[PDB]
Image (cartoon, helix red, strand yellow):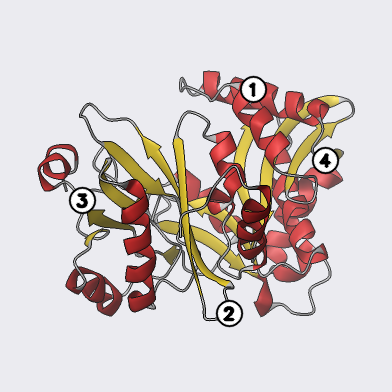
Amino acid sequence: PVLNLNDPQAVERYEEFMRQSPYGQVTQDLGWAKVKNNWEPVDVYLEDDQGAIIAAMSMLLGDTPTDKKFAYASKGPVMDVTDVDLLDRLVDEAVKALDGRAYVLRFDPEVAYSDEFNTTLQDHGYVTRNRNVADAGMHATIQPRLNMVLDLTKFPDAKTTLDLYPSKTKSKIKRPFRDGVEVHSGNSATELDEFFKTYTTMAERHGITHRPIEYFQRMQAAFDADTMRIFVAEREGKLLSTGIALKYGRKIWYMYAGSMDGNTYYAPYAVQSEMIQWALDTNTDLYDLGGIESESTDDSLYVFKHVFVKDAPREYIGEIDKVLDPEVYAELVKD
């Protein structure tokens, strides 16, 4: 069935399934639609024999240069996507709800890539985009397929961040604190302003754009202090670096960051240490540092993230496309 967003009770039942699911994703929470307020939301789900929700997909529809919309379910759907028969049923429900308005329904779930899974998906009629497409550019995947994820379940007795690392790394992490860096966290308007200042400074320093502050304000209003947390690192009254982390489902995700110009006394390391500590304190299974361009020292993102994740980066299946309008798909999507 399709979710009636104006039915408070239906909405809550949908949310409860999402929040309690081991496959839950913050970008699949109905709150994500409130953040992406310039996109159109359409959500569907399936029920078992008892009428209990067993699978759900939150879609956001975007505009294109054509008469069709782009339907995207970021890191969804919420279920075991390898159960392709169930997936098809959920997707059939989504296509019904789209009612011919989109040229494609794309979803990029956080499931491991494998030749067998890629093949099955194609066998079921989907078009997959992973090892067969450019690493970067407007043709690359929306989300990076390679991600640096720390599996905390490998350290069941870990009490603090330092317990997860070898001495050489313990030293790197201890440095900022040794030099006076202190981190405070929360999800108040003041923490947001601190983040925004470092965020925009960072953007200007690299000559890149940045999202408006309202984007983050909507995020703060959509998620509570137990879900969204802003970490601010300072040294003797001086703002140095910050980071925003989201706790949802089985992981805490490091999503945004910012650092001032000049000397930052390795503050970014202290921010990471604190986010990881939050994961340990809440018994969260995974800590996700996000994507990398490539597993190489020639990649700055990899170099930094490799300090906290020594295991191989996780490689996801990529984008799974349910083509609805072939002509438009060929025009707007290429390898």
Q: Secondary structure at mark 2?
A: loop
Q: Which residue is mark 4?
A: 186
Residue 261 is tagged as 1
Give the CA distance from mark 1 to mark 2. 57 Å
Looking at the image, tell me whether mark 1 or mark 2 is earlier in sequence order.
2
Labels 1 & 3 near each other (Cβ < 8 A): no
Between marks 3 and 4 in the image, the one whose residue lies nearer the viewer:
3
- Residue type, mark 3 in image: Leu
Query: How many labels, in total?
Result: 4
- Residue type, mark 1 in image: Asp
- Residue type, mark 4 in image: Gly
Between marks 3 and 2 in the image, the one whose residue lies nearer the viewer:
2
Looking at the image, tell me whether mark 1 or mark 4 is earlier in sequence order.
4
Q: Secondary structure at mark 3?
A: loop
Counting from the top left corner in percent of width and height, residue 140 is at 28, 45
Q: Is residue 194 above or below residue 248?
A: above
Q: Residues within 10 Å of mark 3 (few under 14, many from 20)?
A: some
In the image shown, does 233 or 82 lie closer to the viewer?
A: 82
Q: Secondary structure at mark 4?
A: strand
Looking at the image, tell me whether mark 1 or mark 3 is earlier in sequence order.
1
Between marks 1 and 3 in the image, the one whose residue lies nearer the viewer:
3
**Quick check: can you spot residue 142?**
no
Give the CA distance from mark 1 to mark 4. 24 Å
Residue 249 is tagged as none
Q: Residue at x 67, y 77 (%)?
A: 153
Give the CA distance from mark 3 to mark 2. 32 Å
Q: Which residue is mark 3?
A: 324
Labels 1 & 2 near each other (Cβ < 8 A): no
Give the CA distance from mark 1 to mark 3. 47 Å
Q: Secondary structure at mark 1?
A: loop
Q: Residues within 10 Å of mark 1 (few under 14, many from 20)?
A: few
